[PDB]
Image (cartoon, rainbow, N blue to C red; front, side, top):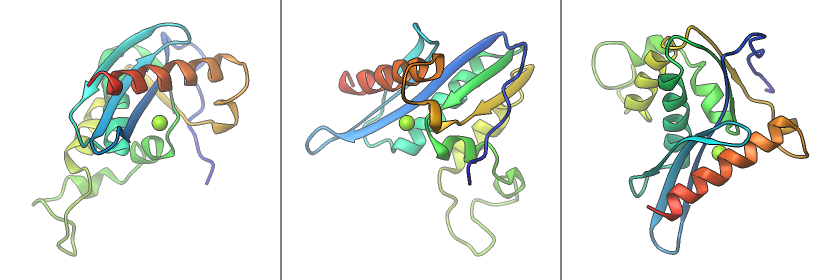
Length: 157
Ligand SMILES: [Mg+2]
């Protein structure tokens, strides 16, 4: 409870990611975004039905891919995203498609990509600090910018 990576002191990039998924009355609309404090560096309207969790992972994976070879500090408004980047990768890499007990592995394909994407950046820190997602600081600013951009990419699905 309440865990996070420490931000890299000399980061090349400082981004905020967010996945948004909601029903616009009947249909499920999802969107992902990677932004700075003032600019949207990447946004994409997502396939209908995409869960908020899957969207939050897609956003984060995308940020990692764009930060290849660089030092990245990325903030996630999701507890799921940070937690997912700290799962026991070993499980997602055993032989077969299912868990040991024989069930399906939730979001196996995204998590597998997230895990690979993790080492594209030269140095990486995934910060999850809710106490600053509100108010007026670079973080609150950045959280709003990303939650807004993702929200909009969905609305324009
Ligand atoms: Mg979110």
